[PDB]
Amino acid sequence: GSPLGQDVFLDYCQKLLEKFRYPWELMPLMYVILKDADANIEEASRRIEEGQYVVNEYSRQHNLNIYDGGELRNTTRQCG
Amino acid sequence: GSPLGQDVFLDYCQKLLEKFRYPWELMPLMYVILKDADANIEEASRRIEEGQYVVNEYSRQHNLNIYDGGELRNTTRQCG
Image 1: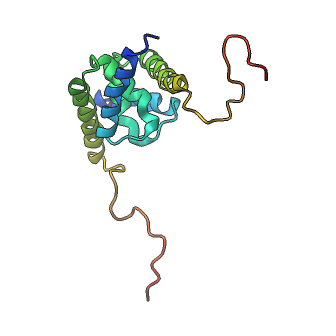
Image 2 (image 1 turned 90 degrees about the vertical axis):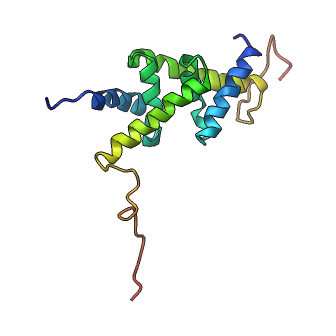
Image 3 (image 1 turned 180 degrees about the vertical axis):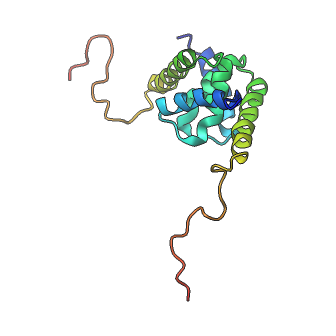
């Protein structure tokens, strides 16, 4: 009787949170994700990443990144 | 992969972001959520909210953070 159920659903989220090093204010999102991923972190963690990769890749598609990329070309190589 | 149609998936993701007024770094989450909610914001917005309520509701029950409105801070107060 001491171990409840809902508290556990949050436990799993606590991991999906510390793993992605997210602040404590993003708990409602780790909650829905696990809610859709059958709460299987091994599955949900595979979604967020596939997500980070999307967002991070999406932008790099429009070349809208003034970071220190440095090496940036295609096909063979311009000349530098 | 599958560009064009992918740009829109970000359009919905954006609303889910501005509506909850989330920073630009939480796009990978608004991405997974819509991915399972058929990307139907009207369907996902129901999860996140029900999510904010869970975390928010789950907290006021133990009075963890939810803003103290008092012992929050102090900095200084040497008036007299």
